[PDB]
Length: 28
Image (cartoon, rainbow, N blue to C red):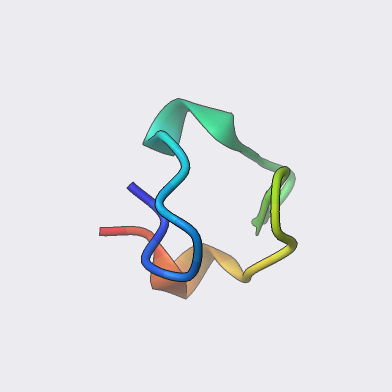
């Protein structure tokens, strides 16, 4: 998941969370 908004890991792409824009480091 994305720690900054809680979107599902499957929603990251190109090094960012494609929902809220967070960087890849914030995924857990």
